[PDB]
Image (cartoon, rainbow, N blue to C red; front, side, top):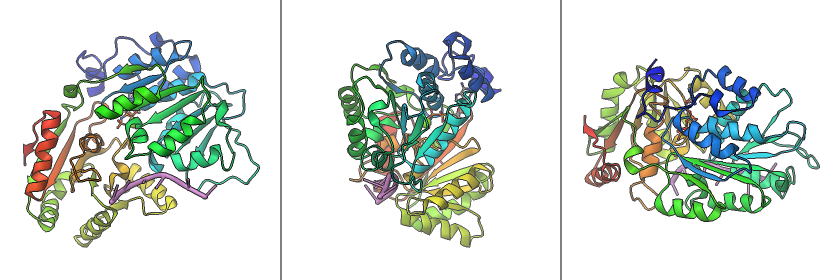
Length: 392
RNA sequence: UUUUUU
Ligand SMILES: Nc1ncnc2c1ncn2[C@@H]1O[C@H](COP(=O)(O)OP(=O)(O)NP(=O)(O)O)[C@@H](O)[C@H]1O
Ligand SMILES: [Mg+2]
């Protein structure tokens, strides 16, 4: 409905000149697409697919806004290249976090379901295969530690047979701060002829430069600064001078933000669990998710939040990227995003608020400012994006 | 700090 109107508007990133039929996907892939409920490509899908499906295959570094369909663009490229007759990994997709790997894997299964023979392996924590076992599935989705184990020490995968390598959230996967060391070690194991696809909603300048040097001869799709922020996510702030006041303000807002699901973002695992415990003392049911939890607990909590069994997720940056829950209508930055140094983290900011307003929905983001220093950070973020954040 | 392997 909003989607139908937006896909008719040439100013929207959801608009495509061409239909799925005109993109010339394999018929089993068009089946997967229409079964997903898709009607028309978004812009990134219609722009990236021809580059990725050109023969000979081409490398791509591409940027597109939050919630514009980057996942299906890359999944389709992986699925187009696989030969379901060869029973070994041919495609490798890396994600920065456990829940994101699980989520994407689900998309792969669903879009590839009309290739009865195609099967998916999960190279994630808690996923063990006896020694001397080589993996049979043609596609692998994983997080970097495990995949890097699977490739060499344990030898479950021959990396020299991989023909498509995908980095989702490509800028944190290759950043020195992020997963650079594991990603580049995995990459070095690939054969020369392997197609490399990097997708993100953001690339800091030096990361953009670095991607051009680790990806041979890439095509590039890059946004202008003004294009990065969505008109559909309203940005506010609340001025407060203490943790307790923020919590107070949060208590104040909680009805208005709980109409539809919310995610709340904290700087540390410890603040995350403190906040979740304090909200439960007020009689609110919230679910806590952070990387100190066991994977079985992490999996069960994200699934319950997806099922609407939990309305409020209190979390760390573990959920900042890529997590797609269509009912999330509010994002709260309880803490403002800062890098390891404590400088303002523009990229994370944009990904956190991108949890809401997915694929044509509207959303709201509320920043909790607790100091002058925090206020400095907020003004910095606003200047980076040139998008004014209203006082609430 | 946040993630991230057996
Ligand atoms: N052509 C399409 N038509 C309708 N819905 C779509 C289409 N492509 C993707 N979607 C839905 O769009 C939502 C967001 O897609 P997703 O691929 O997660 O966004 P993304 O670009 O990866 N964003 P981020 O990972 O947050 O930078 C998902 O629920 C998709 O199922
Ligand atoms: Mg994504």
